[PDB]
Image (cartoon, coloured by chain):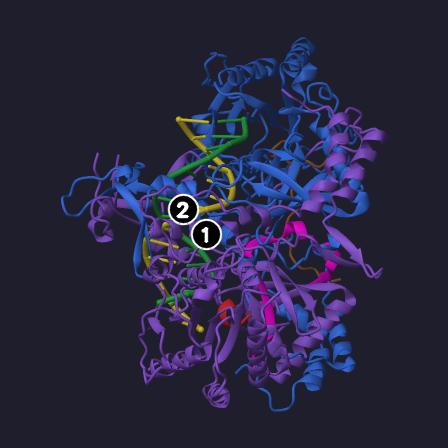
Chain colours: A purple, B brown, C blue, D red, E yellow, F green
DNA sequence: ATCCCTCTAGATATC
DNA sequence: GATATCTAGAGGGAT
């Protein structure tokens, strides 16, 4: 995808109400936060920057008085910290006025001439302006035809949401007409304000990985086989890149070496033998002898051992570090019908399937549960690993219900009941038990990656400063909404005076 | 006290395995 | 504390004999039971202490110098050498070896034998949680011959009882029954099973003794001791436990070539330019983004993981219906109050548990297991205590700590079109599902890799001819399933699969 | 529907 | 000081 | 080139 940012640096954006930040500053902030997301989310996208309204003129097209006061500050290339430095420092407001239609002409010229030799699935042009520059509409027809031919999308970012001068009102008329002529009536939803754009770009792009296609066959016995496809659905995501150890005086990873040594006091690597502990004794156990005596299994098995009631498989026994979603084989109507029958049969009987799962011939076989998961767009089985006999810890804890010492009174129970009502994180709506979540905790990006990217970005731009504190907006999304905290001020006070807590 | 391991006191004796037994 | 067990095997006058001629003698049956305990103890708890003492022989090997009692092994951790030593007497070809190095034909006093066992316990340097003695005998006559020493035996037995010794009994084969309570019923712990029958069948609790146990059997310990904070000033102390933990193969040990001794290993980092050595403070961590190299110190790398102090912070209460079963991230933990840190935590913990169960809500909290780790969002699902028909607890009361996933933890799924199945097809599959119903228990399957690994270690340590092959219980019973289903599969395939489909390709 | 600057 | 358990990094196949 | 697994090193608490 190729993105071209067309920003206005005209004189009209320099001055505004002193009670609010200048639109030039807001556009600069929006563009900077967009580049930060692209840099730390390596996706091979190309970004080009075009400025109109500056004193200098630098365009492939010059002609006469037209196509002037516009500069192609940055060509079409991968984003980098050089762009961030140039945006922060080099870019300064101008003093001239330029037609944003003419700037749109140059943006097409940049995106058309510099796209040769490369394949782009999408093409976008972003316009940052306040529509306060006098201009003449005399070419609109050829632009609309050009965009429909080149298949390039547009977005507009105005300092006001969709007390303005008629020039802005008149300028709004053309941009409304353009969006209608390009992408219909819902094109009205593709015009944004600097405030809401700032809100949507306050966080870094979430780490995304593509689950691989894992084909297998769901076997029930020997004469029944269903072709299935499994993908990893939920897992503990890790960082894409790890830290690299480099020398402190040259900053090179090739100038250091990591090695292991064995002492009894010096032993060579070829004079050691693998061994195992058997009680108080040590027995030699050769690695080559191990693989001869290792458990051997035929890999890639998805076999149903049997079906049991859903209530017999408690959620607290789930093990493993992944959740698999099992779909039918791609482009297979016969397999889709067969798998659908199994899913609906399990759901109607409220049963689950106990299956044996092995990733491949090098994988340890597993025993898990496959329960139906039916939605209005798709249906599939969900596989979660189940524990073995050796993985269960049989601990015993003293009971609390029949304890005289720790029996709460009726007054203490009432105080706790009041707290739970006040600290509710969900609300019923429409009188139809429609529970909406006031704190989903599932749409929240992981704060670990947000903090890490903030420190990396700060160090790169300012290599001689300490790490900044955690961003305020990070804390806000890690805390419940303010109305929840306010409502619990009184019930929490009652608990503090009713439950005597003493630290020994 | 019934429900204990004669080998390891403090742990209840574990029922032996046998996997799937159809009804 | 460490478990301690002492086996006391008799060889007085007739434990090398059988009423039949094709079954095991009492002596080697007891030896087989002892060997099974060593193998079970090695796998389960290698830290326990075990010993074998023989009484009624002609010789004596003990630190007390009392005749007719032989201590083959003192209290120590079990090992492969001890099992091999006991193998010298297993069955035939070892009875004469036992009757040559040792021998029957000497009178014994049971009072003195308990004294030797008591002295063995006192010699232990470690702390013993349980001190047990297992009697292996099938003959109760001599105590009736001399009541004077019989009175001393029960007098000594009472002394051992108040000391903390829990003496047990394991009767062996004897014609005419074991005539219990003629002299016994006052030496043993007599906890239960006071059956007046002479027990013509002479194996009461040797069946489970021979049942080998292959599991880690870890004792109870708290994973962490955190503080549950309702707000900044209301703090209670709770303990975190893991009721499920993935059992792993024991790590291999590096051994020297000929002398076969463990070797300590350490990792050193050196610069290849000079061949010297580099301290951990002489290197920096680096990453590459864009076209720039970012350099950070080791301390700064750790300091960017610090968000909150360890503990649980209450965010709010969420209805249980808002927790998705398919939103599983990692194994759940168990939360139980701890009164040894904050006095009064149990009272507040129980009140929260009671109301949460009544209103069917889950306490959503921010979880920081320890210092310098980014927090997760967890839900404390209430969990009521479950009791079986034997009044034995099976589900402890407390809170179930369920990890919730972030936006980064969810993967996008490929687009597929829904294909609804006709009711006829669903009906046929319902019959198939009903045919293969079975009752599921959490302890119904064993890890095939771990079970096979334990057999391999046992075979090599005991130089057996060939390792025992473990039966894989996770393998589907295709023969049984095919018989149960019958013609259902053929009808279902005809209803769904058109007569040109090839599921194998 | 996120596209353009937001994707 | 030893053991247990989560985390990080390293080695090896299919996609 | 990333994806996914099992194996083999560092590191924080519980007792």
Check if mark 1 and mark 2 are on a common chain. yes
At 52% from the left and 50% from the top, the residue drawn is A447
At 61% from the left and 73% from the top, the residue drawn is A189
From the image, which quarter does the N terminus of chain C lie in?
A: top right
Of labels 1 and 2, earlier in sequence is 2
Number of labelled discs?
2
Pointer 1 residue? C467
Tags 1 and 2 touching, CB below 8 Å: yes
Q: Taking C400 as reference, is A81 above or below it?
A: below
Magenta stretch: includes residue A325? yes
* Nearest the eye: A282 or A6: A6
* Nearest the eye: C144 or A179: A179
Task: Give coordinates of residue A236: x percent, y percent.
Answer: 52, 55
* Nearest the eye: A246 or C31: A246
At 42% from the left and 58% from the top, the residue drawn is A240
| Residue C495 visible in the shown view | yes
Q: Chain of mark 1?
A: C
- How many residues crowd around disc 2 within 10 Å: few (fewer than 14), some, or many (20 or more)? some
Task: Give coordinates of residue C180: x percent, y percent.
Answer: 74, 26
3D distance between C-alphas at marks 1 and 2: 8 Å
Residues in magenta, as a range? A307-330
Pointer 2 residue? C460
Task: Give coordinates of residue A115: x percent, y percent.
Answer: 36, 81
Left or right of A468? Residue A132 is right
Q: Which element carries disc 1, helix, strand or loop?
A: loop
């Amino acid at each position: 995808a190729a993105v071209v940012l067309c920003m206005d640096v005209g004189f009209t954006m320099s001055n505004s109400i002193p009670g609010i930040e200048s639109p030039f500053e807001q556009a600069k902030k929006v563009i900077t936060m967009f580049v930060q997301r692209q840099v730390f989310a390596e996706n091979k996208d190309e970004i080009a920057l075009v400025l109109f309204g500056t004193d200098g003129t630098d365009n492939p097209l010059s002609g006469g008085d037209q196509y002037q006061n516009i500069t192609v500050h940055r060509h079409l290339m991968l984003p980098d910290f050089d762009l961030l430095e140039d945006i922060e420092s080099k870019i300064q407001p101008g003093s001239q006025q330029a037609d944003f239609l003419d700037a749109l002409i140059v943006s097409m010229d940049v995106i058309q001439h510099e796209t040769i030799g490369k394949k782009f699935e999408k093409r976008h042009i972003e316009i940052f302006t306040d529509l306060s520059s006098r201009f003449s509409k005399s070419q609109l027809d050829i632009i609309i035809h050009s965009l429909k031919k080149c298949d390039i999308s547009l977005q507009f970012f105005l300092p006001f949401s969709l007390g303005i001068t008629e020039q802005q009102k008149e300028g709004l008329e053309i941009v409304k007409m353009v969006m209608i002529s390009l992408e219909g009536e819902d094109g009205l939803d593709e015009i944004y304000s600097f405030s809401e754009s700032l809100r949507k770009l306050c966080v870094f792009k979430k780490i995304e990985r593509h689950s691989i296609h894992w084909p297998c066959r769901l076997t029930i016995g020997s004469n029944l086989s269903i072709r299935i496809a499994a993908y990893k659905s939920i897992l503990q995501e890790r960082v894409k890149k790890t830290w690299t150890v480099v020398d402190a005086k040259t900053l090179k990873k090739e100038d250091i070496q990591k090695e292991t040594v064995y002492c009894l006091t010096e032993v060579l690597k070829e004079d050691i033998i693998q061994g195992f502990r058997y009680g108080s004794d040590i027995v030699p156990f050769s690695k080559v002898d191990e693989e001869q005596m290792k458990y051997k299994s035929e890999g890639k098995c998805f076999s149903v051992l049997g079906f049991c009631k859903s209530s017999q498989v408690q959620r607290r026994f789930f093990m493993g570090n992944q959740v698999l979603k099992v779909f039918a084989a791609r482009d297979d109507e016969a397999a889709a019908v067969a798998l659908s029958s199994l899913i609906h049969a399990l759901d109607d009987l409220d049963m689950v399937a106990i299956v044996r799962y092995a990733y491949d011939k090098r994988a340890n076989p597993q025993v898990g549960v496959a329960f139906p998961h039916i939605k209005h767009n798709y249906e599939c089985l969900v596989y979660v690993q189940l524990p073995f006999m050796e993985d269960l810890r049989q601990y015993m804890f003293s009971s609390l219900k029949n304890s005289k010492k720790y029996a709460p009174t009726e007054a203490q129970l009432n105080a706790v009941d009041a707290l739970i009502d006040s600290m509710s994180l969900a609300k019923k709506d429409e009188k139809t038990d429609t529970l909406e979540d006031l704190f989903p905790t599932t749409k929240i990006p992981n704060p670990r990656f947000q903090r890490l990217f903030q420190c990396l970005l700060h160090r790169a731009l300012h290599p001689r400063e300490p790490l900044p504190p955690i961003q305020q907006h990070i804390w806000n999304m890690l805390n419940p909404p303010a109305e929840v905290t306010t409502k619990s001020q009184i019930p929490l006070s009652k608990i503090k005076t009713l439950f005597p807590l003493i630290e020994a | 006290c019934p429900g204990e391991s004669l080998i390891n006191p403090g742990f209840k004796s574990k029922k032996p395995a046998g996997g799937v037994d159809f009804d | 504390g460490r478990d301690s067990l002492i086996f006391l095997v008799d060889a007085s006058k007739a434990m090398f004999e059988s009423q039949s001629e094709d079954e095991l003698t009492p002596f080697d049956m007891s030896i087989q039971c002892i060997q099974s305990v060593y193998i079970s103890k090695i796998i389960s708890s290698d830290r326990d202490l075990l010993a074998v003492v023989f009484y009624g022989t002609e010789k004596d090997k003990n630190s007390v110098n009392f005749k007719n009692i032989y201590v083959l092994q003192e209290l120590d951790n079990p090992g492969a050498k001890r099992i091999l030593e006991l193998d010298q007497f297993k069955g035939q070809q070892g009875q004469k070896r036992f009757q040559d190095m040792m021998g029957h034909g000497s009178d014994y006093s049971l009072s003195e034998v308990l004294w030797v066992c008591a002295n063995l316990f006192s010699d232990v340097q470690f702390k013993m949680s349980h001190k047990r003695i297992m009697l292996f005998t099938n003959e109760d006559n001599p105590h009736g011959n001399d009541s004077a020493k019989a009175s001393r035996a029960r007098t000594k037995a009472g002394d051992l009882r108040d000391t903390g010794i829990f003496l047990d009994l394991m009767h062996l084969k004897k014609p005419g029954g074991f005539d219990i309570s003629l002299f016994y019923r006052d030496i043993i712990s007599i906890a239960e099973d006071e059956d007046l029958r002479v027990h013509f069948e002479e194996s009461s609790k040797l069946e489970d003794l021979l049942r080998k146990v292959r599991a880690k059997e870890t004792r109870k310990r708290a994973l962490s001791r955190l503080k549950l904070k309702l707000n900044k000033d209301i703090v209670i102390s709770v303990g975190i436990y893991n009721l499920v933990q993935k059992a792993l193969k024991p790590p291999p040990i590096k051994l020297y070539r000929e002398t076969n001794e463990p070797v300590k290993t350490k990792t050193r980092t050196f610069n290849t330019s000079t061949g010297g050595l580099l301290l951990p403070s002489d290197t920096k961590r680096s990453q590459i983004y864009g076209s720039r190299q970012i350099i950070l110190e080791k301390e700064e790398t750790e300091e960017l993981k610090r968000f909150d102090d360890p503990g649980l912070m209450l965010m709010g209460f969420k209805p249980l219906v808002l927790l998705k079963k398919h939103h599983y991230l990692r194994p759940s933990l168990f939360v139980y109050p701890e009164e040894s840190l904050v006095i009064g935590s149990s009272t507040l913990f129980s009140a929260l548990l009671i109301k949460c169960l009544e209103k069917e809500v889950a306490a959503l909290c921010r979880y920081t297991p320890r210092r310098n780790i980014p927090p997760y969002f967890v839900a404390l699902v209430p969990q009521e205590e479950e009791l079986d028909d034997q009044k034995i607890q099976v589900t402890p009361p407390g809170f179930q700590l369920v990890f919730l996933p972030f936006a980064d933890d969810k993967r996008k799924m490929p687009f597929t079109e829904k294909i609804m199945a006709t009711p006829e097809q669903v009906g046929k599959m319902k019959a198939i599902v009903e045919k293969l119903r079975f009752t599921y228990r959490s302890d119904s399957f064993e890890n095939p890799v771990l079970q096979q690994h334990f057999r391999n270690l046992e075979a090599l340590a005991l130089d057996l001819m060939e390792p025992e092959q473990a039966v894989d219980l996770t393998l589907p019973k295709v023969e049984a399933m095919n018989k149960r289903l019958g013609s259902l599969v053929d009808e279902f395939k005809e209803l769904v699969y058109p007569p040109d489909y090839n599921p194998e390709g | 529907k996120p596209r353009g600057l937001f994707s």
